[PDB]
Length: 223
Ligand SMILES: CC(C)COc1cccc(-c2nc3cc(C(N)=[NH2+])c(Cl)cc3[nH]2)c1[O-]
Ligand SMILES: [Ca+2]
Ligand SMILES: [Cl-]
Image (cartoon, rainbow, N blue to C red):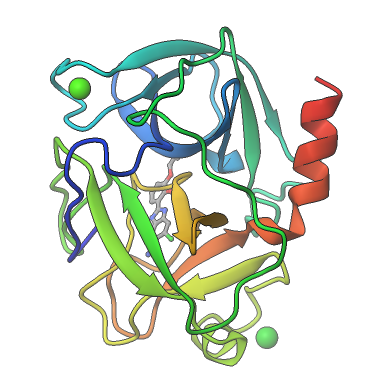
């Protein structure tokens, strides 16, 4: 997160860190045994870390659970990043409490101007690499489709939306990939791609979760 603030320990209880010996992507807990992340964060050997604040110190509240299976969307296109969503089933269910809790899926898509909370342990520099130890937060609005398509002409599909600041300076970045975009208590987006981080007129692009609720529910119900 570039230009954001320290969230405060466990104030984002649905945030998870995907770990393979280091933090490589974020994710969101949607029920005690399933996490939603981005398809491009897929790899084998994933350990899901819940209740984290400092990812380099065991401070208490952490639950480390291995992923039993990862389900990348069948129509995921790695070249366009269209359908960039993945579901991860945990080997055992997590114990939910106030520090580890799931976030709700939306019943409707959000409108432009909706203010959302983006969080993660991704890079904090737009020019260079500085990864934080604790969770960072950023409040950002969903932009209109016209501004999004004007910034990325020919690259935005109906399963994507832009959120952020066109002046640059505040944005999500590498490492935040896979994590949550929560608006009014509902998970509306997944950190997917963007041109650099916090650059002027190049907002972040997010997977539009409201278009995948039936797919998520049907896939969880059959696995
Ligand atoms: C290990 C695998 C997940 C590699 O993934 C990545 C490697 C390098 C950069 C990114 C990345 N940069 C990103 C920048 C932005 C943004 N400008 N808001 C967003 Cl929304 C997602 C990004 N994802 C990224 O997701
Ligand atoms: Ca920790
Ligand atoms: Cl277009």
